[PDB]
Amino acid sequence: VMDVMNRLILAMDLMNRDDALRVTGEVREYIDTVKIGYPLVLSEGMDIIAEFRKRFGCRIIADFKVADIPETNEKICRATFKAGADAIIVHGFPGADSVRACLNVAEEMGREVFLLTEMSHPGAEMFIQGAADEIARMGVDLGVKNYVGPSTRPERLSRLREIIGQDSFLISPGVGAQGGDPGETLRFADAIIVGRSIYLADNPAAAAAGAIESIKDL
Amino acid sequence: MDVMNRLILAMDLMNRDDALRVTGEVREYIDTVKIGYPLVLSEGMDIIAEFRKRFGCRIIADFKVADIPETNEKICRATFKAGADAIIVHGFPGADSVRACLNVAEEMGREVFLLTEMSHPGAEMFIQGAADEIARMGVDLGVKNYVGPSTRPERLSRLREIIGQDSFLISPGVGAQGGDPGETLRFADAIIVGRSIYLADNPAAAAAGAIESIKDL
Ligand SMILES: O=C1CC(=O)N([C@@H]2O[C@H](COP(=O)(O)O)[C@@H](O)[C@H]2O)C(=O)N1
Ligand SMILES: O=C1CC(=O)N([C@@H]2O[C@H](COP(=O)(O)O)[C@@H](O)[C@H]2O)C(=O)N1
């Protein structure tokens, strides 16, 4: 599994190149893995991935929550890996064929797929939560090794960890702004994803250092 | 929304030259183009403005928005800033995530299309069982634009029943995936067609032929 420095992944959702680059550079000594999503990509282009690689020594997880039909999913994965992303996050709710399409491209291109099971926001309780355990089981059956689970629901995150096993890699968002606790989340997740608590702080470096300090024993 | 010939082109080619050329070859048959991530992630969001400059067509950003509310808001803002007239959002992530999109659309004068049931086989695993409820959620939220599967006419008909004749419904899965143009239009206001047109030997004839099959429709 990828060796995430300090078990902390930065969710870089700022929407302008200058600010995104500044903040990421300021926390560079604490984080070597950055999650780049559509807020930044749709604002600055896929070349932002290239710029991050050039400026920082950070792995890039493209958080695109791929959720289309198999044929389109394959195209999205190809374009994303072509740009330099180390991994891509895919939704499991659209079914097994859609996930398999992503896995096939990842295998062919030598990259990784992260399967998003349950989400962290309130709305996830409406439809996703009830399908989450089966989506996770589906991931295991398909050979998925990397997963995403919610920090906001410890009981659900714990169950997801059980389903995927200790060998699987699990990252978890919802820490900080959404209410999740760093340490508690790391009881089940290999790494925590943190966005606003760091990138909106007056001193992102201090925010990152503080978060790491609170989980130093972990 | 008034879609010319009830036909929406799904432009999923991945290079600017081919995308612009093919769209230009069928421009006389359409006035609405669905642009998704295959093209956007390959050529950039500036491609939307380019399409409006060259064709003056309506642009539906098929981004199947499926994030938390906060992120959904940012995605919609960036998308509408690029010139998209509408955006497609997944309903599976819940009401709050859809509401976030509706708010931005209202603020920027755009439309939100709610994707209920999908057209591919995998949709039967989790989405289909929640589709009717997702559609009712759309009705409760005031959603007026929906997306349903051409590949399952009975499911598309049910979606139409739930949302009513007043709502706008577009449907993908026509052609390559097995859906029939005419049958799909019995329930949907417009059909979405990708490969059957942009992958055809002669895209113009494909589009012309498709419209011919639904001539008196
Ligand atoms: O269930 C999930 C999945 C996910 O990726 N995310 C993403 O994780 C990040 C959370 O950021 P934040 O720490 O709440 O500011 C954002 O980029 C979200 O889009 C989430 O919050 N919940
Ligand atoms: O359920 C759905 C939703 C959707 O948007 N689509 C999209 O509709 C288009 C269908 O293209 P095609 O006619 O099968 O080539 C693609 O851009 C898909 O991503 C789909 O096929 N099924």
Image (cartoon, coloured by chain):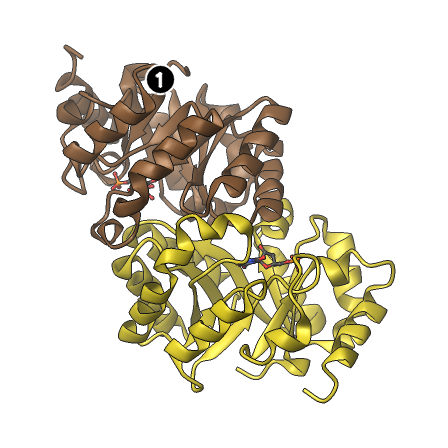
Chain colours: A brown, B yellow
- Quadrant showing the C terminus of chain B: bottom right
Left or right, A12 with respect to B192, comes to: left
Q: Residue A132: percent from the left, percent from the top?
A: 30, 40
Front residue of A208 and A192: A192
Q: Residue furthest front?
A: B154
Q: Residue A8: percent from the left, percent from the top?
A: 28, 23
Which residue is at a point 14% across and 22% down the rendered structure image?
A: A183
Residue type highlighted by circle 1: Val
Residue B174 location, quadrant: bottom right
Left or right, B8 with respect to B136, comes to: right
Q: Residue furthest top?
A: A217
The answer to whether residue B99 of the structure is visible from this angle is yes
Front residue of B81 and B192: B192
Which residue is at a point 39% across and 38% down the rendered structure image?
A: A20
Front residue of A203 and A210: A210
Q: Residue A133: percent from the left, percent from the top?
A: 30, 37
Q: Residues within 10 Å of mark 1 (few under 14, many from 20)?
A: some
Front residue of B9 and B133: B133
The answer to whether residue B20 of the structure is visible from this angle is no
Left or right, A16 with respect to A112, comes to: left
Disc 1 secondary structure class: loop
**Ligand 2 quadrant?**
bottom right
- Identify the chain of the residue marked 1, using the numbered disc in the image: A
Q: Residue B190: percent from the left, percent from the top?
A: 59, 76
Above or below: residue A65 compared with residue A60: below
Above or below: residue B24 compared with residue A48: below
Question: Which residue is disc 1 drawn over?
Answer: A4
Residue A167 location, quadrant: top left
